[PDB]
Structures are given as structure tokens and as C-alpha cells.
Image 1 (cartoon, each protein chain N blue to C red):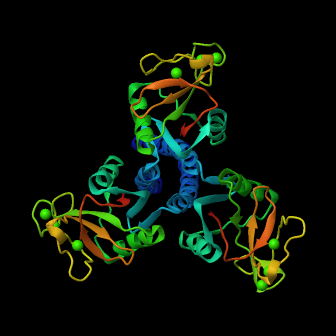
Image 2: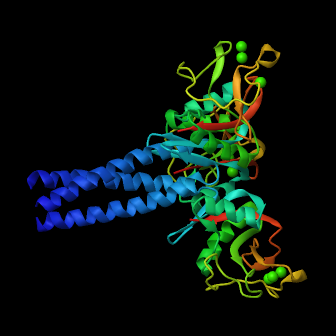
Image 3: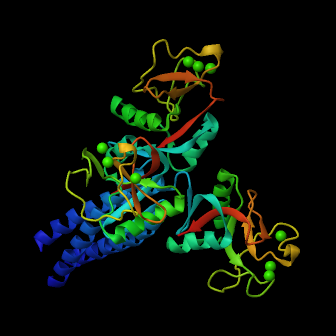
Length: 152
Length: 152
Length: 152
Ligand SMILES: [Ca+2]
Ligand SMILES: [Ca+2]
Ligand SMILES: [Ca+2]
Ligand SMILES: [Ca+2]
Ligand SMILES: [Ca+2]
Ligand SMILES: [Ca+2]
Ligand SMILES: [Ca+2]
Ligand SMILES: [Ca+2]
Ligand SMILES: [Ca+2]
């Protein structure tokens, strides 16, 4: 029993070391292209791509396109967009049913921050969504190129 | 004994929370300049350099130039090459014995994906190896500049 | 007991795996924009900004502008500057009292590596500090754009 006790004490020190070391690396890793908010992490690729390409990049990386589900998440995402000074694509589209935006899973939106008058399906061909540097949303043509930002 | 149990129960909760956090941060880390395959991790510096300089960058970083040892590893590396649209240097050279490519350790290749007609030692001076966006290999002069991709 | 001893072995296995995985990840993260020295880590954003903007970026990331406090730290920082071939801003300034450089906290410098003749407050308007590829320091106008390097 004393042997196991010694083992536990050792593990406690090793875990404490990992926690401290990892806490430091979290900050290092997110600088300058990442943003943590709650349990979610947004990270930009630093370049622009059309929706389909951006979506694939995020999915293959084990995440998905930025999908802010609260004002707080949206504000965090906005910080990255502002820092890079490039509007970015969100994950939602109304490709299936015009006028009804959904997440990649098909679920309807639980949050939105549409600019006044949006979505307006301008030209009758805007089924993707972009977030501006001011944090507001606008439906935009999926064929256009916007900043690639994924969430993990 | 009873106190040790709860101590173990607690410590493991912390470790599993650490495992989850670490796993999330690893995915974030690899986007968009890295690729994991098995226990190996490829990461590109995002710029080009001549072989000697590229090799030094990887060694100083605690790794080595990309050394795909299987079709799976080659495919993973190919993803970075395609993403950057820049052919990359591999670690192998036939500088010691012309025609015989080896890893930095001196060991002979256990896998190769030479493009048709390669390695041809063009000009009688191609002792380094580059991987194209199509995943195939070609021997090339070490003085040329290619994408820097290290493996860890 | 025999069950506790079993749980401990599993826990030990999880911690040992994390130590190996974390160590590998650290190397990946630092390549190619980071440098570890002592308990400090320098990381460059890979781009240039005026002092105020560079300072805010580091602060918002949970760190601060590079603040070498020893020859060892300065040498580590110098590596990033050399690697990017771009002089970088340090955190210190004499904005409060001309001729007296201080850290962000307000404390006086505990180490300096001024190039010959510096600081010279050229034009009567140099209150910020930059580090050259040779590791030496020079006071520079805060409005100029230099490589952003933060410390964590
Ligand atoms: Ca439509
Ligand atoms: Ca639409
Ligand atoms: Ca619109
Ligand atoms: Ca030769
Ligand atoms: Ca040759
Ligand atoms: Ca050839
Ligand atoms: Ca002054
Ligand atoms: Ca001054
Ligand atoms: Ca000066």
C-alpha cells in the first residue's frame, strides 16, 4: 500500500508539471491566429478560399467552419477577422431550402447577427454567410473567396 | 487506502481532462500547416530553402526533413505539398554512394515513389530528392530551393 | 487494493503517453516561429506592426512584447530575428522619462545590449527599442513598423 502511495505522489507531480507546461503552450499556440472562447477554439488559415474549399479544409482538419452560437463566440471570431482585416465564411448555408439557414448538421440557427436587411439573397444567388470586421453577418455567394476560419 | 482511492479517482479525472484539452489543441496546431499520420507529424515552415539550410532547420528544431516510409506517410506529406503548391525536399540523399539513396542515419530506403524515369541523376549532379504535388519523387540538385517540411 | 493497483497502472500509462505526446507537440509548435529559453518562450507573429499595435497583440494574447533579460534570452530572440531577417520591437521604452528605459511594469532595465552609440534619441523622437539581426539594440521611433515577437 505504501508502494502505491509513493506512486500516486509521483503521478501528482508529473500531472502538475504537464498542466503548467501545457497552460503556457496554449497561449503560445493561439498567437497570432487563434482565439479561445469557452470550450471552443477558432483558428484561421490566414488565407482566403471559396466556400467549398474552405469547408473541406476545416472538415479534413477535424473541425468545421466557424459557427458562432452566441454573442460571445461571435465577438471572439470578430477579433480574428479584425486582426486579419478580412471577412470570413461561416459554416451555415440555405442551399437546401432558400431562406432557411442551417449548420452542416441540418439544425436551424440558435444565434445570428445579421446586418440590417440581411439575408437578402442578392442576385438570387447568395446561400453562404460571411462575417464582417464589424462582426455583422451577410449572406454572400459561395463562389466568392473569404478568410478561412475553422472551429475546433 | 480509502483516501488513496479518491486521490486516484481525482487525479485521473484531471488527466482525462488534460487528455481532452491536449487532443483539441493538437488538432488546432496542425491546421493548416501540419499533417499527422500514425505517430509521425509533418509540418511545413511555409517557405523554400536549399537542402543544407532546410536540413539544418529541421535538425535544430529537433526533427528531420520529411522522410515518408510508406504510401500512407507519402500521401499525408503530399497533402501539405498540394496545399502550398510547392514541391518539397525529402531527407534522403545519395551523396555517399551515387545511385543509393539513404536516410540521414545511413539506412537504405524502405519505400520509394519515384516518378517514371527517376532517379536519373541529371547532369550527373542530383543527390537530393523532391516530392511533387502529385506525390511522385524526383532526384534534384541539392542547391535548388524547395518547400521546407520537417517530421517530428 | 488489487483494483487500486490496477487503476494506478492505467493512470501511469496515460501520464507516460501524455509526456511523450506533449514533448513531441512542443517541438512541432515551436517550429519555425518559436524559441524556448529557460522558462520563457518567444514567438513571432511573422509580420510587422507599429509599437502600439504590436504591444496590444501580445497583451491580448496573454503575454507581452519580447523582453530579453539576459544574454541567453537575447541570443534566443536573436535567432527569430535572424530567421525572419527582420528587426523586432522589444517591450521597453523611455516614453515616461526621456533617457530612462523601463519594462512595461515600470521597473528599470536589468540587462541591455545597446549597439555602439545607442540609445541616441535620434531626431528627439526615439522612445521604443528594436533588436537587430546581430542581437544589438537601437532605440527607434515607436511609429515605425518592426517584427512582432511576444514572450510567454
Ligand atoms: Ca438559394
Ligand atoms: Ca439564399
Ligand atoms: Ca447579402
Ligand atoms: Ca552524386
Ligand atoms: Ca545522384
Ligand atoms: Ca531527376
Ligand atoms: Ca521621448
Ligand atoms: Ca527617447
Ligand atoms: Ca537610435
